[PDB]
Amino acid sequence: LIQSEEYVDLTFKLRGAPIPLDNGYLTYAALSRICPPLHELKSIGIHPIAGIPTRNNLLELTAQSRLKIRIYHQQIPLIYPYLAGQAFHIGQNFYQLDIPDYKPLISSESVYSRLVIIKGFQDSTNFIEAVQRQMDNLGIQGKIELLTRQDGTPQRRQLTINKEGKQFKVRGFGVKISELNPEDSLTLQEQGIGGKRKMMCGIFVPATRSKEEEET
RNA sequence: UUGCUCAAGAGAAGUCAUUUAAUAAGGCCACUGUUAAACGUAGGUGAGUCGUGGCUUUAUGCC
């Protein structure tokens, strides 16, 4: 019920050809090529693109599909002229961004992260204690829950970094976090957890997306 | 047993051979969607994969 200050969500309407469901390095590299200053930013995150799933491991862009960026509201003039109204290419297709809209950061008792990556922690228990430690660093208190598939197993995801000729394997979990209170909820939403924040993973969102991800 | 009792209009046959509805035609010439305005002030979101790889002190974050 508390709208966070100093942090906003820059949302660009996204249109173009269908894209892989694991954009990650693809979208990040495209934006970095379009926006050189995006590479050197620190406290910025790119939202997972919202669109229905299509065949293979691709993702189809709808009219509601939009590129959303979480950024310090004073750092917008560093990337706005490079992104607002410009176009970026994923693979061989051209994608166009229009004038973005600002969305405030709302507090929620239960928050969700579709993907959390911590280096060197692959099992569930070590990952859980690592996220507890990360909460301890930021001084946030809450109960950690892991998103599960239809079989109840904790859900894992993989990030493919196509750096140079070799392709890289970075993997993590998707967690659901509640019992946060609005202040710590906003703190976790801005700060995020884990690494690879610009890599379309590690940021947070309300638990409605948690249930939606649980559905499929 | 009925002005009746019985009783095949039956056999066979190409409507055929040939013919351009053809020669010619501009839907054409003309039109202003003219003239004027303070944004005042308060309307929200749809979804994968499975066990360390180049930096960096395991850390923990970058590609």
Image (cartoon, coloured by chain):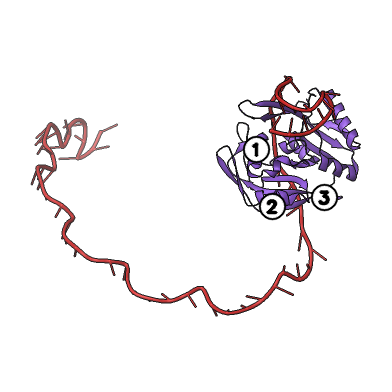
Closer to us: A201 or A80: A80
Count of marks overlaid on the render = 3
Q: Which residue is mark 3?
A: A6
Instruction: Label 1, secondary structure: give it.
Output: helix
**Looking at the picture, do discs 1 and 2 lie on one chain?**
yes
Closer to us: A80 or A145: A80
The disc, 1 or 2, on the residue closer to the chain's N-terminal end is 1
- Residue B9 location, quadrant: top left
Task: Pinpoint the chain carrying mark 3.
Answer: A
Q: Which residue is mark 1?
A: A29
Query: Is there a contact, CB below 8 Å, between mark 1 and mark 3?
Result: no
Q: Is residue B41 above or below residue A194?
A: below
The disc, 1 or 3, on the residue closer to the chain's N-terminal end is 3
The tint of chain B in the picture is: red
Mark pair 1, 3: CA separation: 26 Å
**Whole-percent x and y of residue A215?**
73, 35
**Whole-percent x and y of residue A133?**
88, 30
Q: Is residue A181 above or below residue A127?
A: below
Note the chain letter of the purple one. Answer: A
Kindly tell me whether residue A46 is visible in this rendering: no
The residue sitting at 90% across, 33% down in the picture is A136
The residue sitting at 74% across, 50% down in the picture is A76
Side of A122 where B34 appears, left or right: left
In the image, what residue type sits under mark 2?
Answer: Pro
Crowd class of label 2 (few under 14; some 14 to 19; many from 20; radius 10 Å): some
Query: Is there a contact, CB below 8 Å, between mark 1 and mark 2?
Result: no
